[PDB]
Length: 193
Image (cartoon, rainbow, N blue to C red):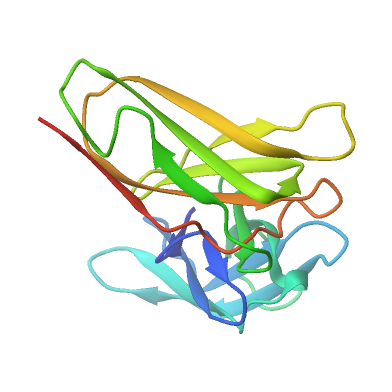
C-alpha cells in the first residue's frame, strides 16, 4: 500500500491536508496509522476504480498533535481488522508557528546552467534547525545549529551547479518540537538558462 500527502506533507496550522492510501491490492478497508506519543488509527472503507484500491483521509484542521509519522494498511476482514504490510512512512509537519526566515540566492534567482548557486536562510530569531524545501520534491535538506544549545541565525545551502529551476522555501524549527515549523519564508523561484 502507498501513501501520499495532498497537496503535500507541510501543513499550515489549522488547514487540512489529505493523506491518500492506495494499492493494486483490492482492500475493503484502509487503516491510517500515526506513530508517536499520540498514536492513533483512522479507518475508511476502500474504493476501487481502474482496478485500484484507495482511501482519502482528511487530516482535520492541522494541530500539533496531528503532526508526526504516518503509515497505512489495507485490510479485508471485519474488526478486529487483519492488517497487511505497512506502507512507507510519511512525515507530516505543522508550519506557520514562528516568524518566517528570509531566503536568498547568492549568485541570484536567475543563473546559468552549470554555474553554482547557493541559498541562504536567515533569521533574527535563532532556530535549532533550518529546512530547505523545493516544490515537487520529497527530500528536504537540513542545517543544524549543532551541539550548541542557543540556535543559529543562518544556514547556507550550496546547491552546486545549476541544472533545473525550482521554487524554494525554508523554515526554522526547535529541537524540542521537530515537527513544528515556522511560517514559510517567501518562496524563491530560481531560474536556469
